[PDB]
Amino acid sequence: DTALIFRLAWDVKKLSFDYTPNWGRGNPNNFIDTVTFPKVLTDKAYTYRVAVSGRNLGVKPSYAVESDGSQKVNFLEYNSGYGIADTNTIQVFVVDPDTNNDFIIAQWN
Amino acid sequence: SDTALIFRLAWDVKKLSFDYTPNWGRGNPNNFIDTVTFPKVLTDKAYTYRVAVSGRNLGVKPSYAVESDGSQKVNFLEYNSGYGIADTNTIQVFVVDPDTNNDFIIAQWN
């Protein structure tokens, strides 16, 4: 990670993020409805792909970043207005709009 | 890509903030380069700095401590026998990871 940080320090100079996954439970509470990141990058129109137990649910338009700098991924938009049972594995991948490559950014189970 | 690297880093560390934009400080006369400052350095280790000038290694020294604003200055006069560096020279600054003794380029003049 130290080598990665300093590669990035040379390349981009300035970087600040918080991608700590904050999982939102629904009602009933055994459902995972959302994941929220406290401080996302905003230089590109990043999108999120969701996989549930290894199955692609695909990509949906991104929620606007809030004033506090946070961004929410709502699994209800990916799953027909329902959240995901917490016994499942849930993966969120952030998509680079320049390449269409995606990178793991949140995993439940 | 940097994007790939950023999101790899983000998955590993979650939360990070730095600024290594080189801020060159000129001497007297001002065609001499005397210092470089980085606005927000990493504070997780006791990082030191290696300086090279036109291909000549001036070695590794600790810098001054991280300031209250989070910045850190490297003073070339300490490395270069008490004198700044004519700005026609190439000046390279490397951060040394004290855990591995690996070097990383972090500033280059010319």
Image (cartoon, coloured by chain):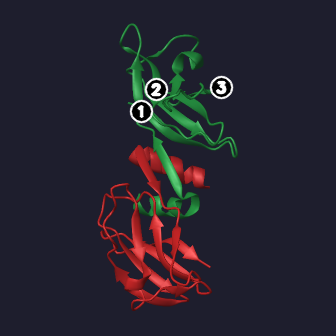
Chain colours: A green, B red
Query: Which quadrant holds residue A18?
Result: top left
In front of the other: A65 or B31: B31
Is B46 left, or right, of B54 in this rendering? left
Q: Are marks 3 and 1 on the same chain?
A: yes
Label 1 or label 2, whichever comes before in sequence order: 1
Q: Which residue is mark 1?
A: A21
Front one among B70 and B7? B70
> Taking A88 as reference, is A81 left or right?
right
Q: Position of residue A22 (x, y in %)?
A: 40, 28
Mark 3 is on which residue type?
A: Pro
Of residues B66 and A69, the one drawn nearer to the viewer in this rendering: B66
Q: Which sits earlier in the primary sequence, circle 3 or circle 1?
A: 1
Q: Nearer the viewer, residue A33 or A18?
A: A18
Residue B87 at x, y = what percent?
Answer: 59, 83
In 3D space, how far apart are the residues under numbered discs 3 and 2 (Cα atoms)?
Answer: 15 Å
Image quadrant occupied by the C terminus of chain A: top left
Relative to B58, B54 lies left or right = right
